[PDB]
Image 1 (cartoon, protein in one colour):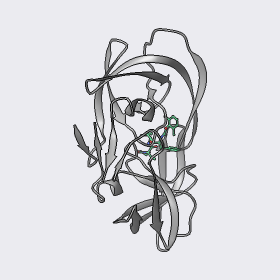
Image 2 (spheres, rainbow over the protein chains, first blue to last red):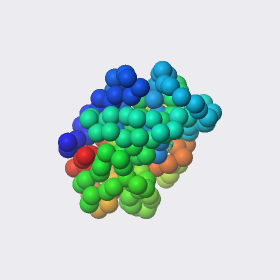
Image 3 (cartoon, helix red, strand yellow):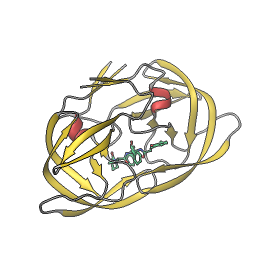
Image 4 (tube, rainbow over the protein chains, first blue to last red):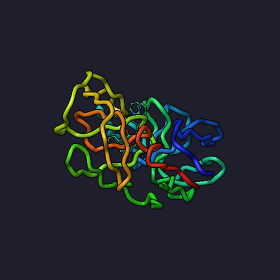
Length: 99
Length: 99
Ligand SMILES: Cc1cccc(C)c1OCC(=O)N[C@@H](Cc1ccccc1)[C@@H](O)C[C@H](Cc1ccccc1)NC(=O)[C@H](C(C)C)N1CCCNC1=O
């Protein structure tokens, strides 16, 4: 789909059996999700945004379906105000910017 | 241009007679620039990211040229680690996401 930017580019994802809304985010290197129930092992990590740092859990090779396109990769889980799909996954669904 | 997302989507901007590099950022409502010399009047404001909140200065109707496309709008100025072009300007240069 082509997505214009008059509203937040929010898409429906399926991750770990659950349905969520997430922001397609070209200004995010990584993918950050709200506190959620994920299976597997992790490594403590800190994500750094505007205004400072959040402690996150890092899960590798997690399956996600973003607007019906499958991607496998790293997902961060922690106290983000909004679910963020970052460029690590955007590249996998063939996502481009166009102007 | 079409921009893939294997690297940060950094473009050259001209703002207030100066040249800078900024991130085309679909996950940003607003445009935030590092501390810089801007002319005019302002209003104190707080921008809120992943780590909490930064105090910024809000300037209205500021001309920016982003990859050679002029846009006029609100620019926020403050202690961001990266220059961010938000959807408020991205819509003016006809920027879309495509997958
Ligand atoms: C950079 C990065 C590296 C690794 C992993 C991750 C998730 C990374 O990205 C984290 C990040 O905050 N990226 C920002 C841009 C970024 C990259 C590098 C350094 C600093 C920032 C931006 O794209 C997303 C983030 C989302 C958000 C946060 C809080 C509330 C609402 C939305 N959006 C915002 O902060 C914007 C700002 C820029 C005007 N924002 C805040 C006011 C409300 N609305 C809004 O749109």
